[PDB]
Amino acid sequence: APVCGVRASGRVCPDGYCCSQWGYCGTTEEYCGKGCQSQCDYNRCGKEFGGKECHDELCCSQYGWCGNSDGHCGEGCQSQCSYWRCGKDFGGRLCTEDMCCSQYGWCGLTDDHCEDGCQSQCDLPT
Amino acid sequence: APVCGVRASGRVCPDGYCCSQWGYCGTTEEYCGKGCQSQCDYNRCGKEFGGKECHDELCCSQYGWCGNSDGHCGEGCQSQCSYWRCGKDFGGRLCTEDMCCSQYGWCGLTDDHCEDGCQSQCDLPT
Image (cartoon, rainbow over all chains, first blue to last red):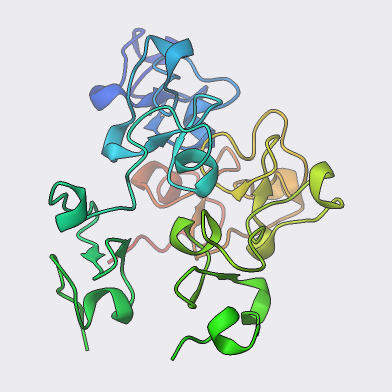
């Protein structure tokens, strides 16, 4: 049964999640896209959105979208643009998602990131 | 020794992957962003890229980036926009990654998608 929206006493979603047109909470297109009832800006950010920053330390694109693609963290990125950088050369920042910080200062979950020279969170099955 | 790039006699990565400044193959910002040596438009798509479609049936956002996160399959999507849809209203289409098809024709792994009304692949994760 619906947990949010017009079919749920106009209740909103916890943690700022989007309430889907069908009355469920989430952060994907189904919930935040067409038909979203409330808190539809969960994945939005930037100057055009009260200057809000993204959840999960994600980059804010020049179009006010949260994400970690080069389209979000690269040219035009508005905030939290150093999502993929880490280590001694970057204030000792630790990667999110427990990613390994490579010798070159890049977050990743591959062997070459967790192998020789890994700076932090080097745990990786092998 | 590097597997791609100038240090590999100009060899490019397989399957269109980006070659990083360090000579390795990947699809994230480390490989496709600044310093990328070749095949840097791996995640690009749309009108600005010869009408290219995305790999892994991902949606092409209005900004020409491949993905399935919020902002890629909704308004402005250029191609393969039905990534999250499934069910009888869609000819019986099944979800990828073994996701459940909800009663409303949306793919997901949450209880409401796999429970009452689920149309296919309702095997809740264990």
